[PDB]
Image 1 (cartoon, chains in turn cyan, red, yellow):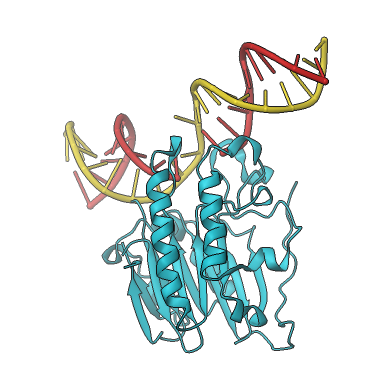
Image 2 (image 1 turned 180 degrees about the vertical axis):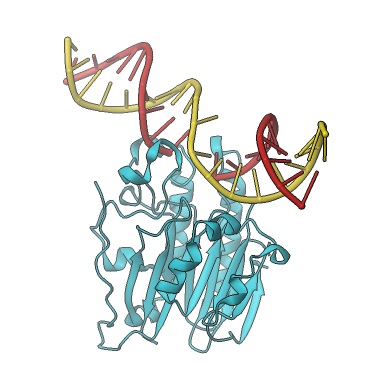
Length: 265
DNA sequence: GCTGATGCGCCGACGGATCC
DNA sequence: GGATCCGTCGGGCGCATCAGC
């Protein structure tokens, strides 16, 4: 079945208007994503904060169009395997890289700490599943020592469909990367240990067919055969500020679609 | 400097057993 | 004997590297 994303809710349950728009997008090759007009979609989206994953591009190789973004001038970049980026209208107080460089950017703002993550894939044949489980454990601990200080927002490709609702084909993908019990359990452990909450599922717990990733192969996107691998996870103190978590199914330029968070801060 | 090849990383389609 | 479940496998796309030239 096809998915139509509900309209943007820009008011919090407590009555507070949205003041912060965060966009997250695994661009699957920043240079290719730009040739596919992905920046033009970002300009239409007008995010205060843009988090990019799978850049596969060093900073010295970034197209000059990224430095021609007047509303996203504060740019933080890591480094054809991974690569993450954080672009912000306002300068964050503190920026760090890693979980204690290429998969994690931590940006501290006045009322919140933003973490963007390109979580390592378990691999075809699950060759890197054990490293992912150790990675998952290292990230969870690192995030626990960040949430204690200030509210946390975590965005990006977590390389996991938490539940059967997060993918079109749960039964045949239970031994595939993204739907292993090991990865699903790691996500549940991040939600309970930090603690954090799945923004989209908190808002839409019974909504199926909502995916953020489709294989370029076998025309998967045109058939909505996909997976929800991209998330906005929020500390429970920030749930009162949650106005919406959106899935931008129509934006192209990658096998991953953009996700957008509206916060009332 | 540029093009095309190859390598590497990153599951939906379909064939074949099997069992109500 | 057809629904279903598992196992097997070609393939889209980006980028690095290489070779040619």
